[PDB]
Length: 375
Length: 146
Length: 48
Image 1 (cartoon, rainbow over the protein chains, first blue to last red):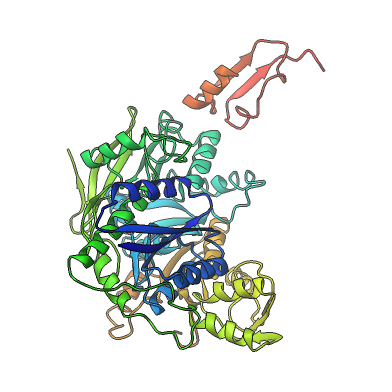
Image 2 (tube, chains in turn yellow, orange, cyan):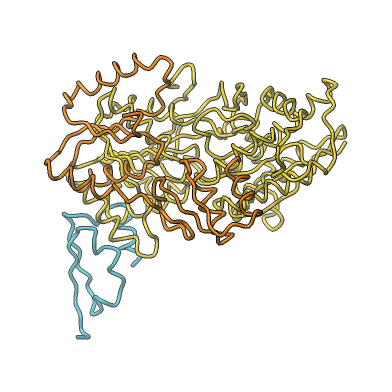
């Protein structure tokens, strides 16, 4: 039983691919084996993504695992919907209801809004990055109307990096007109460190300031720098290292050879990589529930050109979707469940605060219970 | 997807230039293909957010004219009802300028409003625009949503 | 430089603090770090 699948990994996704490999090994069974066809392309380039998709489609794959950007996301959601091809991705959730798309990343929009009310914020600065879509930006802006907030949204994304200093100085100059002491950083693990470094330089990391890292990887970045500054730092963690499940994973992950497995010789793991590992498990349980359900879907590498007109969707794809979406197992990112669309449900996001001794979970966030503190 | 086919179809037919339209979703497809295949694309649609070669845009940038008008009326606190159809390019414009010119903008996405029951939403819309007694509104929408 | 680095880490380089580098090489070390901190820094220079 050889199930061919596609793999679209953006150049630089070392740990993500390393986690993708480990998953292939941990979830390999005799009943059937998964054959990944890896394609390293610039995820941002919409054209390239189109080729990589049609290429993996002509090779006759049953499902595709990859990533997309705020620019190429529409290409994937569209093609996968037309050709009835299933697409599993750890990337940011789609802004809507796009069929044939499985999203590993839970919606943070809810957990963020809840945290703001917890600290009882009425006036705060919102530094955002247009990389993962302004989905969360619209969230805080719309809620700012109801909850009556004075949000100071600033696009910290279009900042040219070959001279990005007179921009940060002019950034916190506007954040001083209203004496902003509460900032929300909605950026990637990289853009966050850049800001954190600047914050320490200008000395806005002392007692009185309060930062909120708006991502699922609070412990993914370096916090030792703004840890003793005095300013309170909060965030979100999706990979609970207190779970015996995750704890066991790290035991083997931290030991792996960094030569064969790039950026895999650490005690921690980026949430993007952790979702990749959990993605493999979902695809395995899905293709397994099809064998035990006596459902024939097999084909050959002659699906034809994806640009075929009229484009005819192979009916076997409808079943592959109902399989992945029906999957429900336990992974590094807590309980994994899906709805009819592909958005994760019944999940848990731990709320984190940075103390003197280090990060510490002060509670969690459920889609049904909102925020709940753990004494 | 459809836009991709229509482009490759007109490309196989061997055209010298392409005139059409794009949405906030398909815009990336056009700008990308036209840039790779060196095909010229003329469009009246909204200007691209950046510098994409092989694309001719008939629509001038309104971002500038809008910001200038706001200062003319000397607005410091206003509501900004926007539609995500033509990209949040102008939304970012007023938000970024709100930091410098020091404005209290109340941005509200009036786009995702489901039209088969869109009434309890408008009533709840001007309910928030009454907490601060907003009397100055900017409608950034299409001729229809307006 | 070791002390200056530590000073910035703990944030004792902001307005209110005053440091005096007791050596003949004030510009010999890196000052760009505690330059925008706010704390006043003085020293001595022998090479004009």
